[PDB]
Each structure stands twice: as C-alpha cells, then as structure tokens.
RNA sequence: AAUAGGAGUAGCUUGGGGACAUUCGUAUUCAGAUGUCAGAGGUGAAAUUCUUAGAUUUUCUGGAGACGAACAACUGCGAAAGCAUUUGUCUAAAAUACUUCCAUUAAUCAAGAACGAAAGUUAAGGGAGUGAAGACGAUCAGAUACCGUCGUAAUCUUAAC
RNA sequence: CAUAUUUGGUAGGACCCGAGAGGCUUUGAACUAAGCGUGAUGAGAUUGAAGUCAGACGAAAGUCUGAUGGAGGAUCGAGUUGAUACUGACGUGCAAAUCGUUCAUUUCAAUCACGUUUAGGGGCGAAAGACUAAUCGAAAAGCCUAUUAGCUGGUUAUUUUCGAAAGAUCUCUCAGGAUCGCUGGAGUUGAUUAAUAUAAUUUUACCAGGUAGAGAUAAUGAUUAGAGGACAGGGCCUUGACCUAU
RNA sequence: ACAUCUCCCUAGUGCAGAUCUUGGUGGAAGUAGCAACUAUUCAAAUGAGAACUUUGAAGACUGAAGUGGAGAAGGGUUUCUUGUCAACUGUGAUUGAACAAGAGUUAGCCGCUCCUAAGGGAUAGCUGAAAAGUGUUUAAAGGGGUCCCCGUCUCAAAAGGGAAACAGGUUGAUAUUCCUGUGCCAAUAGUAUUAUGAGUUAGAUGGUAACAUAUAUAUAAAUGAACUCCUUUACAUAGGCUUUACACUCGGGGUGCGUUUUCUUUGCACUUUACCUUUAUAACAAACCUUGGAAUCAAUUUACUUGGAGAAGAGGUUCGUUGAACUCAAUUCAAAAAUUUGUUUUGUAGCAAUAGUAAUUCGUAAUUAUCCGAAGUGGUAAGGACUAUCCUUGAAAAAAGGAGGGAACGGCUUUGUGCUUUGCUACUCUUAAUACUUGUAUGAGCGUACCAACAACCGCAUCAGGUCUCCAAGGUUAACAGCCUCUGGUUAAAUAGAAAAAAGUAGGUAAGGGAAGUCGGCAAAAUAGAUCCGUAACUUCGGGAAAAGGAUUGGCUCUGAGGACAUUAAUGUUAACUCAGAACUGAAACGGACAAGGGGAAUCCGACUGUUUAAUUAAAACAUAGCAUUGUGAAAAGCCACAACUGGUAUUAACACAAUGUGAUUUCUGCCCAGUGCUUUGAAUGUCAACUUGAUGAAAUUCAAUCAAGCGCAGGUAAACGGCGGGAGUAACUAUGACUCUCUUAAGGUAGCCAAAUGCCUCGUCAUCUAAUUAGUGACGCGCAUGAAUGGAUUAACGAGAUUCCCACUGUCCCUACUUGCUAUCUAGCGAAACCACAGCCAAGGGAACGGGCUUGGCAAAAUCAGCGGGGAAAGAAGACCCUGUUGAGCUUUACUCUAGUCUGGCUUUGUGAAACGACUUAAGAGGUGCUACUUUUAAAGUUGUUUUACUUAUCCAUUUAUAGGGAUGAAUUUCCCAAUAUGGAGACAUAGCCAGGUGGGGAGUUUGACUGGGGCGGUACAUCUGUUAAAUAUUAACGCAGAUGUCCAAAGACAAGCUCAAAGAGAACAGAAAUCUCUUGUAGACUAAAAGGGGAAAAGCUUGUUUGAUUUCUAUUUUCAGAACAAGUAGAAAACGUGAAAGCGUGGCCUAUCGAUCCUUUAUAUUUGCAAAAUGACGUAAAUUACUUACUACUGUGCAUAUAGAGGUGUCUGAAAAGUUACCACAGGGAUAACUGGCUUGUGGCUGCCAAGCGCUCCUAGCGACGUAGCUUUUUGAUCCUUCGAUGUCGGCUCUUCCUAUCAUUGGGACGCAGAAGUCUCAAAGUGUCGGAUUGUUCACCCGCUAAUAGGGAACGUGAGCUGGGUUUAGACCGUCGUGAGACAGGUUAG
C-alpha cells in the first residue's frame, strides 16, 4: 500500500512538538563543587504554568558560585511547596520537602521524585504529575541505592544521584473525566497532533493492515511479533497475554 | 435540697470504648540463594494435580499482603452495631468519693434525625491466604451435590453508598 | 568463385496508424489537505447553572418561597459559513456545477486572511481510495520511445493469363503459428510416330467382405401362448416344476 | 521555359475511403436564438445618420450588509485632456476600459526601509562517487570594555513590535506629499568665543508620609565607572457595569429658502473649530499615605467585595482616563502681606478667524452682516474599574527606561620623578547662539496613476460565477432583519418595437369534497409577533416544553403606576419611556403589509454538539467522551524517520509516550487454548549456518565433532483471531416432554433477543390498527444462518436520518377552469451549432430471419406557415454489462521467486593482567587382545583452546561557562585532617565493518492451463484400449453410447510330455443340494492374470518334468503419420544358449491396452580418448660409461571431462518451475460469445378436437367423460444462438390509441336432467362497454366495495428526445451466512 498512519507520525514533518508557548526545559541545577561538598540555599520566586504537563514549574533563583549576582533555573515543583520558600540543594542538605539531596543520604521509606537515572543528569525519572518513587534500601558497602519507579519496577541506581524529597505536584489529574470532545481537543492542542484517533479497521486496505472487508472485522490475529517489520506493527504489540487483568 | 435531674471537683479512677499516628510478632506466600535425590500432594478409597529443566524436604536473606493465637474466663468496655500486638497524641465514659453548685431543669416519645454486622453496589489503590462463579477428577442408577485439585469476583485500605 | 536483379525468409520502426502500462529524471501545496505563526471575525433575541441576599418554617438536622445572579461544544435566528429538499430552472447553459425557492450553520471540535511547513508508490486524510492547480485505485512535465500489441481499421494506373482454401498433424493450442495438402512461376526430361507410358471408365478373369435384408423350430440374449408326457408340496386328483414336439 | 517513345539508369512514383492529416467550404439557416438583475417617457443640442451620445424636464430604482466612500491581492497606463471611428465595442453607436496624439504619479512626519516569530538559507563538523542530506554533533569563529568581558551568521511581517503631522486651500489628471499656516521628530564633529541658569569657596533642596521640586526666547542642567538587578516593550476568553467621544434627536434665538385656494407663531436647510501647547486646571474609577481604633459587626457594588496583616470617619499624595470641564486664566474694585480672599470686566484657553459655511451687497475682485443659549436617546468606538471561565493560562526581540553598586575626580603656576611639595583664586557643569578648521557638516534610496469588479482581477471573453478589510443615516422594529425614505449613486445591462395563441416557465386563485392522487402528503397550503393563562406520557430529574391547548391584540379619549433636582414635614422647579386599568368608535377588524413553529401517537438506527465522498451518496458511515487492552524505566530503551552520518516523538519520562480495539449513561459481559496467532523457561534436550577443531590423504578433496538464534520439545494467553452438536424413548385424554437412553465435540449458544436493516421456507401463526393491511404495532420463536466489547439488552435528550398512523390543512385528486409577468409569435436589427452514404409516402413479400430504396400492389400534383414527438432500429461515444487477450493495474494471502528492516552466531576493531577449566603433545600404572597393536587411570610436565574476573589507555554515553584535589519572598561583586588525562559513568563489553543463519505481503516482481452447445461449477471426452455408432475394402464425428488403462507375474516366462474340461444323469458307509469315489453322456456350454471382442481340445486349457531366450548386437519394416518421433509389434541376420529323441520351437506374457524429448544427474562399458609447452607404469628391459649416452617396450598419478548404454520425469501425457480477488478498476477486441426483442420449433404452458369404458335415479353423449388418441396457438416457460457488443436506453406505474377474438356483459337465436324463476351448454356476433379502492416496486396476487360486466389478448413484453425512477444493475453504508484474506451472496435494507 502506502505509508501507514503510525509510520507517518514519526517522520519529523508536521507532527513535531507544539513548541510555541513552552517555557523552556525542566532540568535540575547542574553538579558542581558547592553542591557536592555541602549545601546551597536558593529562593523560589515564582510558580508558573506549562502548556505540556500537569505539574507546575518552579522558578528558582541561586546566587552564582564564581561570579557576582543571581542566576535563574527551572525546577519541577513538588506538592506542598510555595513562593518565598527557601530551597536547599546538596550533600549536606536536610531531609525536608522540596530540597534536593543525593539518594544515598535518604532514610528508608521516604517518598521522592526527580531521580537521575545515572548521576549528574539533571533529573530524568519521575516528572509527570502525581507520581513518586520510594526509596527501598541502601547496600551494606553503600555506593548503590535501591528505588521503586511508579510503574511497578524496582531499579538500582548510584547513591550520589540526585532526587527531590516529596511527591510531584498536581496529583490526581486523571481522576476528573473529560466530559466533551472540545476539552479533549484542547488537551491535544497544546501537546502533539495525534488526535482524533481513527480506528484502523475502518481505513482502506492501502493505508493499514487491519483495513478492508465488509464487517470491519480484524480477520487475522491482533497480536504481532516483536520481530515484526516497520509497516506491519499493527494492534497489540508483542503481548505476553490478552484478556482481562488479575494481578 | 427529692437514695429526682443536670453541672462541678478529686484520686499512679477504670476499661480488648472511639479516632489518628506508631511499632512488633508469626505462620503462609513470592523471589533470591543452599544441599539433597524420587516421588510428593491429595483421600473413606483414590484419581485430577505438581515432579529430573530437581518437586516435596533442609536452612538462610530480601519482599508481600493477612492475622494478632497462647494468656482468654459462664471476664471487661461500648447506645447498639461492635471492640483484643507496642507506644504516643487527640478524644470521649462510667462508677465511686464529695457538709461543691444550680433548684424541677424531668419521664416516655408519633414527626424528623444520628449511628447501623455480613453480603451487595460505585470508584481508586491493593491482591497474601481464603474463595459464590467456573473448570475439571471422583462418588452415585443419575450428582449440575457432599469429597478432592485448581480457580476468577468478593474478602483488605481510602472515598462514597 | 565473383557480381547484377528477384523473391522468400530473419533482425531492426521493417506495410501505415492504434493502448492499458513499466522505467528514468524533474516540477507543482496560488486550488485543495493537514500542521503551525501573526492576525482578523461572528446583528438580534431566548432560556436561566453555581454563588449571593431577603422571607418562611423547624429544637435540631435541615427544608421550602421571592428576588438577585448570569453558567452552557444550551434554544431560535439574520449575516456568515454550508448544500438538505424541489430528483424545480438551465442542461447547443448566464456557469466544463450556474439560478430560484426551500433548507442546515452563528462564541466554538467556530469562520476567514496572509505568512509558513510537508512532494509522487510520495505527501496529506475526524478515512470517501478522499485530496495533492478542471489531471488521482498512484499528479503534472519531458525522456528511455517511432515502447510493445497472435487484435481493429486502412493498405493508391490498365489490359492479359492461369488460379485457391476453409482438410490434415503438432502446438500453454482453438481469433495464432508451424508443417502437409491444394496454387503460380522457372526449368529440365519425355512425348510430338493416332503410339507405349497413361486413365475418378468399363471388360473378362480372379479375390476380399458380413451392411441393408433374413432368421428365431440355427447359436446368445430377449419373448407370448397352449398340447402331449416320467420330479417337488397337499388330498387315482390339484398346483406345479421338468421334459418333448409346438 | 519546356520535352525526349532512341536506348537505358534511378526513385520519398500513380488514392475515394484510414472516426486519415492540413487548409478551405456547404445543406442544416436568415433558423436556434439575442429571457436573470421591477421600467422608462417627453423636449432640445451635436451629427450624414440617434430607442441605447450629451442637456433639460418628468417618472423611477439602488436604499448605507449600496452599482457610495476608502483600501488589500492581481491587473498595469486601464488615469486625464485633446483628437476620433479601419477593425472592435455580439442591436444601433457621433459612445467607449477600442484606435491616435500629447500629458500625469512630488513625503524627515503615510508606508517600505529596522526588529524578531512560525520558519528558510548558509558557516563548523560529518557523511556522500559527486549531486546532495544534515545545522554544533571533536570550532583556535562575531562583538563589548581597556590585557579583560560578552558571543553562530544571515534572511523571514506592506494586518505582530515599531522615533515624528495636522488643518485649510489648490490642478484637466497628485496631494497627511504641492501652496499657506501652524508644528513635531531625529540627527546636530572638533576647537575657540560668547550669552542661559545650576553647584562650589568632590556631587542641590522641600514634604510626618505617600511623595514633590529647575517655566531659563528653551522645564536645558539635581557627579557617577566596572559589574549586577529589574521594568516597559508584551499580549487569552466570556459576561455585565460604568465614564468619555462621535452619531442621532428635541426645544429656543438668528439667517436664507419652501408650501401658503383652506390650515400651518410653519416644513426644510445653515448656525463650523484640527493637530499642537510636560496642553493649564477641574471631574472621576482606582491605588497609596497621615490621623483614627471599629460587634448591637461595619463599609459596600448591577454583580461581590473589603477590614486589627488597621475598617469606617477626617485630611491628603499619585497614576490613568479625559482635553478649557471648573471662575480657568487674565483683569477690576472691596477686604489682605514689607504679595491673599471677596466682587466686576474680558477671551470661542492659546491655536482661531485672517480659516470654513450659510447669507447679503457693489465692481464685472471688494465689502457688509452671521457663526449660540438649554437638554435628551444610546446606535458606534475607546477606556476604566471589575467578576467569572480553562486536564486550554493565552510570542519574541529590537528599543527604551529605572535602580543597586561605589571605580574616577578643583583650575592656574612650579621645584623633583600621570605622581610629590611650594605660590595664587574665579572654577566645574549645562542649554542655545556664534566663529573657525576638518572631504562639500541637515533630513538617504524606493512606493505614491487607476480599476478593485457593475466592464479594468481569475474563470479561453465586456462571463448573472468566484475574490480579503474599514466606514454604517431616517421611519417602522426585538432588529446592523424585511418594507419605504435622506446623503451618495444609477436610470445600463449580448437588442428594440408591435402583437397576444398554443405550449413553456416564474406566479396568483379557486364551488363541493378533503389524500380518494402518488412508491412516498412530494409539492402546495395551514401555523407564525407578543401578552396573559394553561401544559401530559415519560425522564439519566437536568429536561420533555413554544409541549399539547386556549384567550386577547386596532384607532381614539382618559385614568393609575414607576424619577431627578432645591427651597425650611409642607412648598417649588423639573425627565423619560415602559407598564397596568376604563370608556367610546367601526361592514367583528386590528402581530392587518413585512416579519414568522405545523402538531401529535409510535417503531429502527445512531447517545449527544461535531465531521465527510470539491462537480451523483450528509447517512444508520466517521469522529467523540468513557470502558478495555498492549509495549516500554531511556539515550546499548520503546515507538518511528533516514542512502549514510543523523534524526523525530523529546523544551519528553509511566496521572508518560507509543500502539490498538470499542464507543454517552444505565444494565450486563457465559462457555472453550484443541486449530492459527502472540508469548514465557532451557545446556537434560531432537534438529538446525558460517566459522572453528580433529581424522584421512601426496595434495585437492573427503569425512566427523562443538551450547546461535529459530523451530521442536514444556507451559501461558479468547475486551487474541476465532469457535460455541446430533439422534431416539418417556406423564390419570390426546399433546408436549420436565425425565431417561444414545453417538459425539477444543467446548456444544448461557443472560438475553426476534420473522427486527438479522427468517430461506414466508405475504410465518395469533392478535390489533383499517371497510379491505405483502404495510404499521404487540405477541409467539427447534432461530436457512440471533446473542453477549466482532459488543448484548435498555434508554432521557438530540436528528436536512429510516419507517407507520392520527389530527389540523389544502387544486395532491375527483376535474379541471380562469388569470398575471417573462419567453414563444410578427417585424427591424443581428446571428451560430450538433448533425449529414445517398436520401426520405405506404402494405405485403421475400432477404443477414423488423426495409426509405428491392418485387407486386396501394397509389402519387407546385410553393409553402405553425405546432408536435409515431418512425428515421435519430444524436452523443471504438459498451462501462458478458466473453476474449499467453494486454494490464489496484488489492490479499499459510501462490511461486524475492527483499529493506529486525533477531542471532562468527571473524575483525579489541589493549593490559589474574585465576579457574579443558584439550593436545611427551612419560608411568590397571583392563582386554594377537615382540607388536587396543581400552582405562596416573604425570598436574610443555603447548594451546575455553569460562570467570581485575585494570585502564582503545572505545562509547552523559555533563558544563568544561569553574575549588579528597575526607571531618534582605544584602553578600573592584578551619582541621590526608594526599601532591575537564568531570562523571560504562568499558575491551558495546558499537561499527564483513561474513553467516533465521525471521520477513512491511515492501517488490511475477504467475494464476485448455477443452467447454455463454463462462463458472461439474466432467476429461487432454495420453491411451475394446465393442458400438460407421452406411459389407480402407476412411470417418458429437461433453454420442456400454465400458476399460497408469498394473500383475520366477512363473501366470521357456520348451516337451501326459492328460481333458464346464455340466448333466445314474450309482457307492457316515453323506444330506453340496464332501469323495465310480460309470455313462459330454465341440467347449470350462478354463485361458485383468475391460470387452477375437483365438484355442492329442491345446494356447489343466497336471508333470527339465530349465531361464524376460540374452547381446544389427537390420528390413507395420501401425498412427508429415508416410517425422516415441511406443507397441511383424520378418530376419551375427552371437552365445534353453528344450525336445528329432524335426522343430523359444529374442517375454494367445492376439488386441499397460506409457515419456533436450539439458542435467546417476551408474555401467573400452588394448576407445582429452585436460592445450612438458612429465607422473619404470630409469622396465638390454646394452653402455661414468655421460644431458644409445636402442627397445599395446597395457603409466589424483580429480574433472567426453564417447557408448541404461536408469532418475515431465499424466495439460511431442515435456513453462505458478494462487486468489476487483460492485475502485483500465485497454485491445468480439455479435466467432451471454443478459433484451424479433426469427425457427412448441418439449413446457394455454386452447381445441376425435374416441365412449363409465358417470349422469333407469339412461354412452341434457350436462359430462377416464383408458387412449389428433391438432391448433405463440398471451407462458424452454430449447436455440440467426440478427445487433466503434451502445436497438435494461422492470413497473401513469397517460394515450388502435388492432384482435379463443365472448365477460349487452343484441338476436338454438339445446337442456327447462314448469315459472334462476341457470347451463351452444351459434351469428368485436357495434358498444368492461369500474372505486385497501395492501405490495410488482407483472402477478389477495381482499373489500360498486357493478350490466368488472372477458381474454396484440401492437419491438405498444407507450423514457412523453413522464415517473419505487424495484433491479455503479461508487458510500448496515447485518447475517460464506471466505485465513482481499472479498462473495438468483439473501435482506438504505442514501443514490
């Protein structure tokens, strides 16, 4: 046929991210001597909204460590933090909400966010609204630490990786149902052109593997192999099992 | 100043009364190790089941939910439903004692209201064990049952009913 | 052997005209599609969500009544944006989609402008194989290319002479081809001696036949009747079978 | 200029045709036609000539959503004046957007020009043959300060940001642009003078505060560096409220004009004021401050907001609106201070009247007079203060400004090395002017006409089409609607007049009936505005709802209700429009025009609003929220793009991203993992590639062996694809079967549901609706073939949806009639085309089977005019249906062949060590065997292969401005201990390179027999063999007939010998019909491998003996036939044998069937050959000498190849390696070939006979009539395939006419089982007639009703340039069954 709808989405034309009103990337204060050997205290001056994600962004001011005057970063906000709060970052920073600490210095069973998947990477796991990770353990020789990502996997990271004490802001976002189509339109309008979806089975054959027939029947298995080639990947990708959940 | 009533005051008064935080124990189970070697589970009898890719069994680590025995009674508290690990915090409660205060403030109550086991419902988590449904193996003239093996929903917390 | 011409055969454009395509390289997003940026735009009405105030009731919890209020991809509606119905007008049009009347749409999944993004087995698609400049189940342009066609049409002065076939075998063969048959030309040989060769002929000899016919009492198969006799059931007798001549 | 025929060379050499090409031209024809957009008339001028040039007068229209002003894109001199008429200006034309000749566009301020956005193009790298693809991914890169700090370049807005301009006047054509006035903005160098004010003896003051302060021709001037920190620039949507401006209106004064018979203190016009002056002030919403200290809370807005974190009150300060408001300023006099308050006069506040406008006079340019006192409506626009909405929070920079910070700091004279010490006091700022030098020392370049559609654009053009923005008057009014009017514009459209008919088309209107019409209430009509009442089922409680259903409504004349101000409760001045009530009045009418809901009762589908097939389908399709599912923890991942490097999702991170299914709510979501998918474990495990490793060999080779994934083996999975049974028997009647038996499945349809868009049978059965019901609805449900996210069931709301009924209503219909505009018509003017072999009266006949011409008849008389649709198998256009092609294409798959990707192993890149493991080599013991060979253990020897690990320098990822060596909601700038590759991370694994296996409709290329009484299905008649058809040689056909073939056989072959069989009779213990035995009779009735036919008795049969000729080689030939091939034979020959005594006979089967080219492989054969300059037995045998010696020998390495001979197979059998689909389709053809008529025939249907056994009470025939038998007919259905495939428009209804008779009625008769009556059969009869409906797409059918009877037929199945389009037969769609799929359906249903 021709290039299928899934393939077209990737290809860097019109489907590029809806940039225009985004306020710039959220990534933690980069690693330095002052943080590594101690603590630096900063000021949250403002909390600002973001067209991409449910969590609000937090406007954080530091005073520079080798030049005069104040420099501004954008941190992703923990729930329960506030404008005019002092935010502290570093190895000696105290365990308190919205501070930024190495995971090696957590007491067990703390709830955290902004994990760096490997050290110094400025935060890359646990950023969506209402998520958290839990610290589950410290090895006897130290150096590594064991954490739990909110999907349900357990993961082991280096101890000196950063995280932020407290749950990610804007919790419960998908509790509220989207009542009408226009609200869904507005949700996708600030994200990515990906919607309305269009059922693949209703397409002509030329456009998609489910297409054709006279009852909109799938007509062959809905589970396709991990090994499947590019245009073939159709319904339930590489699935372990199908039908309703148990645990 | 009612062996009426309410209120007060007092005691290292009382108690598995309520709530929240908190903490520990054990089995069971999962995972990770460990050593073994043929059967192990299962029963009125057995089979379905699980097992040489090492089951069952041995001991250890880590995880997980559940429950909180024994002590425990012709015992305690709660309006009743109900309530049993540790400590803390917030709460109520009754009796006693009282040369303390108020002075009939009461009794029962259609209307109306608060709470209201268990199951069930709705929603999020959660999901060990148990286990309507269901699936088989048996038992029986027959068995949609009793018995057996597995096994969803429910059982647990939060938020509603 | 060389060479002249001829015809046939074979390759090429190869008797002339004719696809549907396939490949190669480019050119289009002024329409239109979707995305984006900067911007514009939507007469007038109607309903009357939350909150608020006042009144009323009740011991309580609570509940009612009147205002106020101004919510909603709410309602009707010009415009605007559409195209439902009239199978109305026109249908050698006013137009290669127009006209009249009717109708759907109007603060949002809204409409428009301009700028901008994505390009051909590609783009784009709230998905019709829709759309990508009157061109789309594979755009437009030129070239490979006079592509190729067992198929259709056409295929040009005269007189004269001879003149067919529509059988046959083989064929991924049944609209074709090959190859035999049947035809013309060229030539030699022979006849040219009322001849021998010879003949779609008869004759006299001599064979070979199993069709029309004819037969059932000749065989095989059918097939309708009785007559006369020496193996079976019942009570010399009955049904027969079975013979024999019919 | 031309011949050549004397002879002969040479060729792009001879046309009617090709839907030929090109150019020209007719009939059609003075015809079709010149129809939108309300509509013109009279007089005059110009001119040769005026319906459409100009002018006046009328009458009209556009009607501020305009043919009005401006502008954008595009056009491009279209503008203007002057000419002017060859062509054009579809009529005319003196006109003109035509033609000709000149002419016209003026900017510091309006734009562009500058900035950045979505984005573009480049630089660094890196890829790539290059072309190009990428845009910091290994940058020594553009600037600012004065050695330090910033830091990709560049383009991208004529509607975002944006230095500054307005008024009046003026030209034939421009004007925010020229002219006049007034300003504003930006520059404005150095040096020296001057003048302006500041500060000083290096930085002013006030104010409690919020904050204020420079008024100089000019508000100029209030120190400030590095470095910083802000802010303005700069932003959504909704809703109301409020303020100002403009607009509109009213009243009064003043001017002019108008009506002025009658009325009219009148109707109308005019009554002007810009930028600019931080505009001066006032006013007002806020904000903020000082005081003040608040509950019986207060203040307070339309709205709610606000307060001990300080409210009210009282006094202030500021911004923003505004832009002369306010006694504002100036002035005056009265009362003040060593410069105020009170009173007066001025000024359109300056700009400003000199400028405008309306007037009025005189010259023929000059004067005069006017220019202003009150107020309302709220239509526009801006602002202000706000409130609410969002799983949406609503650009950026250029540019400018403010602050923090505190670097730097008299002038002159002078010793000494910018510094130090001495002497002296106007110095430092700062505007503006001036002079001089310095290149010439003030304002760059580009745009500016006109149209902007009605004729300037695009649409082939002066095309009723399309095309962006602003401006918005009066009345009516909810109203920017519709109607009419003012300003402004027009009175022209590709023509006019006259006539007035059919027909057409855009309209009206109809008595009585009221859907009877029609597939269908389509069309048309009815309704409608408002106020006041009244408002159901049902409902997700929100709605349904304007439900339904009523009433009222004019004009006049009154009444009541609703405010604002200011006087000292009363008294006064004073504003709107909206409401409510009462009289009187009239042809009972009054939302009067315009505007403007039909409603109800139900079913089906879709929840909804949304969206879609541009130019046939708006929907039930699609989307949607919710539900449900799946992958993925990250740059060595998911998902996806790219040749490659590299990207995108990602400015991201599981409440995410990606991929699907389903489709609001409510209620539910059963069963099955066998089949196919998908998926999880592995060195026990079968297979499974390269490499490796060993063994063998002279080597090539040849052999083995090893832990890849994959599959297999073991599980998991159905909101994965999907799937979800059959018979019997059984209850006091019968019935049914709870109940039982039974075969069987992976499991056997549960909850539900229904003749539903799902039901074939089927118009199902029963109700009900109706008068009549294939329709509607409710039931019932052994259901061709319902059913649970492929969703089941129900649903309020919603629908340009599908369907039915009921009410209202009507010309839909009875049944049509009248009427109006515009056409048609005639004329003047202008003026095409399709089409066209030739043509054009018929009947019949024949003929390629329906002729205009042909034969025989009828017949046949110019020229014309208007209609019309019978025919011209009328036109269009190489049938789209069907078939055909060794033409295609789209699409699908477990078709054949592949392939990007992906997964996995190996080798490399790939270093450094450590340890463990194994193998191999060399030595010793134990076990078995025949000085030798084999098996098992031991060396822990050497060498080598492997698994685990440590290291980092290779390599890879991340990070930053590459920013301190490791341990113990202010401001912030000029320790101690240990040590002596930017930082982490990962790391010889990746990755990448090359091999190699798997996976691989994601994507590619291609194929997808033939015959064929259409094709497909079925079959094989495709290779063959018998008999028959075949017509007495031979020949010879059909999807003719009855059949057979793809083998079987060491004997069933070969030879000889012996014997005679089947059967029948008569006999013989057990013994019977069969058993064996015997005798007689026994020409074949047996047996002969197998079809069927031939042949066979001292055999060809049966029994027995001996055997292998079922052999090798070669001919001549027969059959089919081309007299090719194979195959099967027949006759021999040369060998060798077998048997028989011997002749003989034996070269497969008693004869007729039993089957296979080339290449290739494979194994046989040989004293045959090759491997391309040579050799390989063998220095063999003799000699010979010491050597490059001489003779002489059929037999001479491995491997490969030949030649000859078999065998491996092509059954579509003289031999391609090959599946489906198209209702999305294309093209070449076909009447060689279907679906339609006509034609032949008439099986089938229909109609008529003849017989006479019977029936008819008795009685053949009154009426009948079996058993039988003969015809007719072409209204049926077939059979057929002659005609048409470069198109005969495919069902039915409507309408309309004619023909027929096989008569239904009517007329006349005859017969009777005929009493009358009723009637049956029958003859002349085609004159005349043959109906209203219900239901269905219907032919047909069935009712119901009328009737005189509701007869049968024909005419290309009469009737589509008459209609209609409901059905069938395009594209969309739904459901079932069927198909893995694409898709299929003589099944249904819907838009077409």
Image (spheres, coloured by chain):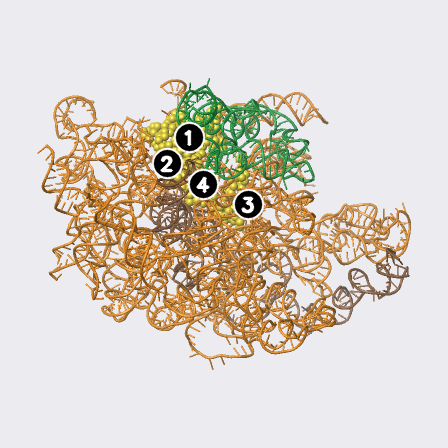
Chain colours: A yellow, B green, C brown, D orange
In the rendered view, tell whether residue D452 sits above or below residue C216: above
| Distance Cα–Cα, label 2 vs label 4 | 24 Å
Q: Which residue is mark 2?
A: A48
Residue under the image location 36 percent in, 30 percent down: A85
Under tag 4, what secondary structure?
Answer: loop
The secondary element bearing badge 1 is classed as strand
Determine the image quadrant of residue A192.
top left
Q: Which residue is mark 3?
A: A220
Question: Which residue appears at 54% of the width and 40% of the height?
Answer: A243
Q: Chain of mark 4?
A: A
Instruction: Tell me the chain of label 2.
Output: A
The percent coordinates of residue D1019 (x first, y second) are 65, 55
The label nearer to you, 1 versus 3, is 1
Q: Nearer the viewer, mark 1 or mark 4?
A: 4
In primary-sequence order, the first of circles 1 and 2 is: 2
D679 sits left or right of A108 in the view: right
Q: Chain of mark 3?
A: A
Instruction: Specify the label residue A164 is tagged with.
Output: 1
Between residue C23 and residue A186, name the one nearer to us. A186
- How far across and how far down the image is residue D1113, in percent? 71, 49
Specify the label residue A206 is tagged with: none
Q: Secondary structure at mark 2?
A: strand
Q: Earlier in the sequence, mark 1 or mark 3?
A: 1
Q: Are marks 1 and 3 in contact (CB under 8 Å)?
A: no
Return the chain for callout 1.
Answer: A
């Amino acid at each position: 046929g021709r290039v299928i709808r899934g393939q077209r989405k990737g290809r860097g034309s019109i489907f590029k991210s809806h940039n225009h009103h985004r306020k710039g990337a959220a990534k933690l204060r980069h690693l330095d001597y002052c943080e590594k050997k101690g603590y630096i205290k900063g000021l949250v001056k403002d909390i600002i909204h973001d067209p991409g994600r449910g969590a609000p962004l937090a406007k954080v001011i530091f005073k520079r460590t080798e030049k005069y005057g104040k420099k501004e970063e954008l941190i992703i906000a923990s729930e329960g933090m506030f404008t005019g709060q002092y935010i502290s970052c570093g190895t000696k920073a105290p365990l308190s909400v919205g501070n930024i600490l190495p995971i090696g210095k957590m007491p067990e069973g703390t709830l955290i966010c902004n994990l760096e998947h490997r050290t110094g990477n400025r935060g890359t796991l646990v950023k969506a609204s209402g998520c958290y990770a839990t610290v589950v353990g410290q090895s006897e020789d130290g150096k590594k630490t064991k954490v739990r990502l909110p999907s349900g996997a357990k993961k082991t990271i280096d101890a000196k990786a950063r995280a932020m004490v407290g749950v990610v802001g804007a919790g419960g976002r998908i509790d509220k149902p989207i009542l009408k189509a226009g609200v869904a339109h507005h949700k996708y309008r600030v994200k990515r052109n990906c919607w309305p979806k269009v059922r693949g089975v209703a397409m002509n054959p030329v456009e998609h593997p489910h297409g054709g027939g006279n009852h909109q029947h799938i007509g062959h298995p809905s589970t396709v192999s991990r090994s499947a080639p590019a245009g073939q990947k159709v319904g339930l990708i590489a699935a372990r099992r199908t039908g309703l959940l148990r645990g």
